[PDB]
Image (cartoon, rainbow, N blue to C red; front, side):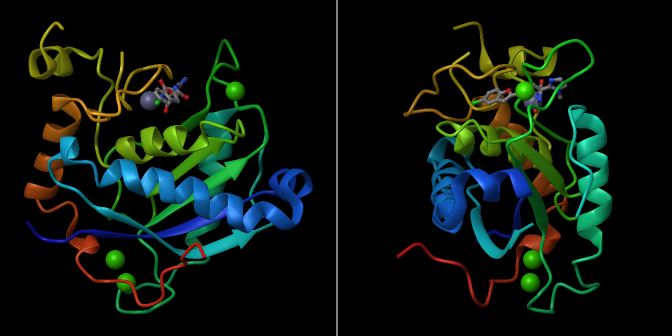
Length: 214
Ligand SMILES: Cn1ccnc1[C@]1(CNC(=O)c2cc3cc(Cl)ccc3o2)NC(=O)NC1=O
Ligand SMILES: [Ca+2]
Ligand SMILES: [Ca+2]
Ligand SMILES: [Ca+2]
Ligand SMILES: [Zn+2]
């Protein structure tokens, strides 16, 4: 039942600034509002409030390898944070949007990357998103699902939890997301356990000065 608030640092690279220009801040808050709406959907079972508290427009090394862009960004974002959650400048997770075509080992179909189950570890609570211009909120929600310890819905543990009957955020590839069920039962279970085990202990304080859309 506890309200959970994820104090979020949103970062946009030079490519995002070059393309969106003056409309970038509004764009990022719109994307994040949409991701936040996903995280309040009842299907998640333990809803959380994704709150933008800091917004940086650019830094870290951004290139084709998603793995090394994520590692670079995650090292870089540490520097902006503060040691204690009591500090207003402290943030719980860092998310980077870039126009760089991010790639895996064999193709560039990837749209983002995050390490799994890291949300209250400031050294590790990181995600990167390739901005496609239309579905970026869904990619952000997928990466943030991983940060909240979620697996893909075609994983073995998820088959048992979902049943037998690709329409959710944690599908392995983007497909059309069910508006009545953005999160599978597997997704809800994994975030619920993560929080029940005390891994969301940094999500309990309420942010001071959230950034709001007009
Ligand atoms: C880790 N990795 C390594 C190689 N490729 C990856 C992937 C690829 N998938 C995506 O980029 C991506 C975006 C998206 C949005 C929706 Cl709604 C549903 C599914 C989605 O998948 N990155 C990731 O986060 N998981 C992966 O398998
Ligand atoms: Ca705080
Ligand atoms: Ca890509
Ligand atoms: Ca916090
Ligand atoms: Zn994934």
